[PDB]
Every structure is written in C-alpha cells, then in structure tokens.
Amino acid sequence: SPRIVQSNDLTEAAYSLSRDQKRMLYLFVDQIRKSDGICEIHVAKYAEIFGLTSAEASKDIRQALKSFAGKEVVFYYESFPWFIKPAHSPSRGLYSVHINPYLIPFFIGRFTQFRLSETKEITNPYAMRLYESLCQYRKPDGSGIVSLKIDWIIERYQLPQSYQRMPDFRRRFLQVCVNEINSRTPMRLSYIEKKKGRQTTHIVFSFRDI
DNA sequence: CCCGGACCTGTGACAAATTGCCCTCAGACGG
DNA sequence: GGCCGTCTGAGGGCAATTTGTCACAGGTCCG
Ligand SMILES: [Mg+2]
Ligand SMILES: [Mg+2]
Ligand SMILES: [Mg+2]
Ligand SMILES: [Mg+2]
Image (tube, rainbow, N blue to C red; front, side, top):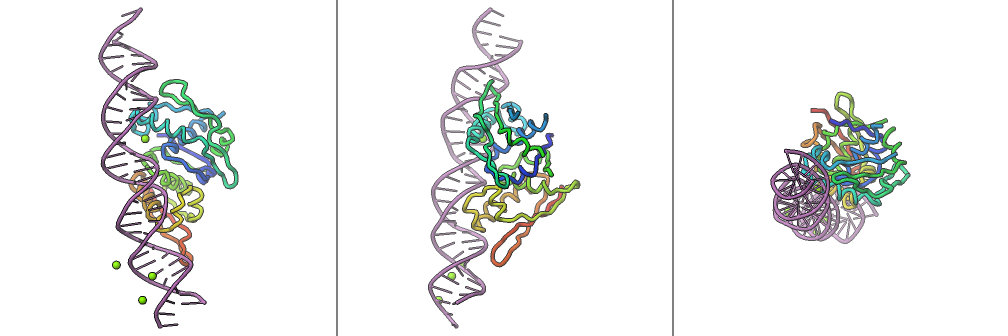
C-alpha cells in the first residue's frame, strides 16, 4: 500500500485540519512527490481506499474542500494559505485543486515516513497528528521513545482552549488518542507524565511494533 | 493554631459537532 | 438508433456517539 513520506517541518507545523482533510492531504503529498501544485482526486478511488460508498465519499470530499478556504499553515514563524484558488470539478466524480506552490519545498526536504494503511482507521485528527510525530522518531525495527512538551503539543496541534486545564487534556485528548492508536494501528503505546512542582510539563512516550 | 486563598486533581452534566446510515433522483454509459 | 436498466455520485436528511466546556467535590501548602 502507498508509502507516505514528508518533511519533519510538516509533521511539526501548526495547523488545524479535519480527518477528511488530512486524508486528502496525504494523497496530495503523494501526488506532488511523484514527479506546479495542481492535484486531482477521483471520488471512486477515494471510496475504495478508505472503504466508503461513493455517496459518502462525495460528501466527504465536497465538505472538506470548501472548509479549506482561509485555512493557514505556520512553520516555526511563517504563515501560508493551503490553497490559492477555489477547488472545482471539471468532470463528474473528479475534483481539481490548486495547492500553494510555496508549500512544495516544505513537503519535500530529516523526514517522516509511514504506510497509509497504518493510519487509515484512525478517527480523531489529533490522534493522526500524534501518530505522525511519533513516527518521526521510530527506529528501523519499529520502536522508539520521545518527550514532547505540553505547551508545544497545544500550539502545534491547535488543541481547543479548555484543554489548557490539565484534567480535560487527560480525559478528552491524551487517553482517547492513546486508546485509538493501541486499537487502530499496528503500534503498542505507553506513556508517563513529567512534573515540575505541581505542574505537568512533558509527556514521555514509549512504543514498539506488533 | 486555623482561616481564606491559590494551586492541583477527578467526575457529572450538558451543548455542540461528527460519525456511519438511509433515501431520491438525474448524469454517463452500454447492451 | 435510440430507449431503458444499471452504476455513479450529488443532494437531502437521521440518531447514536464523541468532543468541547464548565460547576463542584475534595486534596495540598502559603502567609
Ligand atoms: Mg462523512
Ligand atoms: Mg471548618
Ligand atoms: Mg464524598
Ligand atoms: Mg476546600
């Protein structure tokens, strides 16, 4: 199945995208790398890749696409729009998109790589972001260990404001996304909290391959 | 001493958003 | 040649679940 690779600058960029948007983004990065910024998506191919009906695929592509307008990307800083022209459909079942050509060098560069089947069952987009960031540190054999700072997680992934209260961070983000990864990818994940005084400052992740 | 206060934790509630499902009907194609 | 039966996909919706938000109970230490 398709092998996604991407610059670490993208893995660690600041942005807010939905699951459906992130799914399309993997294919854009795949199309671009296999070579101006103009990409294409076929309804019927998307449905087969992610096990959807054509109808629900159509709904997913269409709504995702109009929600890109005005979205911006920050590399730590510098801000860019993803798209510089609205999407449009020349043929039935076919969509054409114009990626910001200044983003090309950030896609292809100190890199991250994973097969697309590893992530296609994840639902929560924050769990996608987390699985990408861990892959950046994985070893050939399939294991790794890394410490991420809590303020940096909040900025980079653009978590919502109430997760600045630590019990909500644990309950609605950390625990859920560790569960999905353990339930939906071939990885087995554990963690421990690093504290300084009363505040929790980093999260330390360990993982192996099944 | 023990207070009110400033931190921290977890949980119960509710509001807002997203999920996989369902139904309709016209477009593009073929037998 | 052209009608109609089928495969697509662009729309309209849903209830059951998940995600986002905040009040309140209940721990500690400070001055
Ligand atoms: Mg959908
Ligand atoms: Mg008393
Ligand atoms: Mg009690
Ligand atoms: Mg008290």
